[PDB]
Image 1: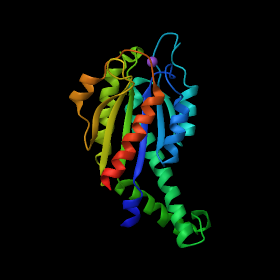
Image 2: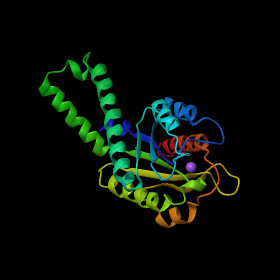
Image 3: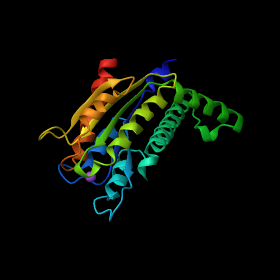
Length: 232
Ligand code: NA
C-alpha cells in the first residue's frame, strides 16, 4: 500500500573504535542528517589495553543528535548488536509514523485506542517493519587503531546485510570507510546494492590515519538523499 511505499527507512550505522580526532564535528553532521528523517546509530568497540583512544562520549552525542542508539560492545558482538539496533530503531520510527497517520485520519494517538485496537496497530507496525524499503549506509572507521578489529567488522557487516535480506521489503546498503584513500576524507566501498561485496570490503578497508567521523556522516547522508531521488 501507499503508506508502506512512503515509509521508507533511512539509517546511517557508524562502527568505530573511538571519538573523532580530525575534521568537523560529527554531532552536528548527525543533527543535519536527522532533519531529513535519517536515523544515525553508533556502535563503539571495546578493544584491549588502556583504552586510551576509545572515548565514546561523542558516540553517545552522535546517536542522541541523530535520533538513534549507541551501544558499546566487544568485537564478537558487533553483528548481533547491529541487527538488534537496526530493527529496534526501525520499529520506533515506524511506530511514530503510524501514530501520526492515526492522528490525521482520527484525532487519536495509539495511547487513545483500546488494547484490542492498539494490538491491531502494532501488527501494522510489524508488517511495516518487514515490508518498507530500508536504505542503510554503513560507515566503517578505518583509522590505524582499527587494524585488528577490521576482520571481525568485515564479517559483521556481511552478516548484517544477509540478515536484513530476509525481510520482504527492498534492501539498499552502501558502505563507506573513513578516512579515505591517500589524503581523502572518506572512501566509497560500494554503492547501494541488495548485497554486500565482500571482496570490496577486503580491498578497501585499510587501517591508517586518524578518524574523520563528521565527513563520514555527511557523505552517508548525501548518499541516502541522492538515492532517494534516484528511486523517485
Ligand atoms: Na581509532
